[PDB]
Image (cartoon, rainbow, N blue to C red; front, side, top):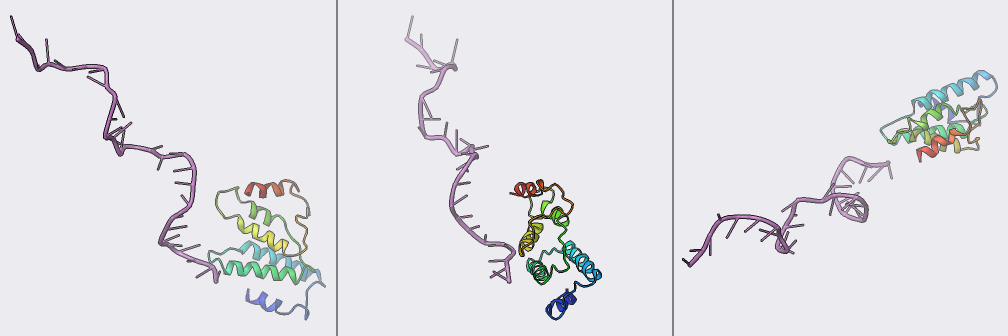
Length: 121
DNA sequence: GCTAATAAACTAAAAACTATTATTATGG
């Protein structure tokens, strides 16, 4: 977290999208962090959420939304609890920018992808 | 020169169905 904060402390100074190496590193680390994102501390968790929001805002020159790690996250097991809501937060981060609501990069079903949410209702 | 009892509607709570209430743990 400290090093990524330092990295994003400047974005106009440097922004990695030239080599595909930096792009895939950014996407892979994005996946890493959004797999790691959870806290019972309710603020450092939101801190990570805002970190991701800032990251995607200052980027997408090298970023790619999985729509799968998120999908399994916000879907949960169709529970009664509030767990999968964390993935829902990702959606806001996803809706933090002009991102496609669900790009079917392969397409899970492109239809029940939102049926999961209307079930979460 | 006869109280052997039973057919007792009463004032019975000894469910609360579903509707606001409130401490908690709070949050930044």
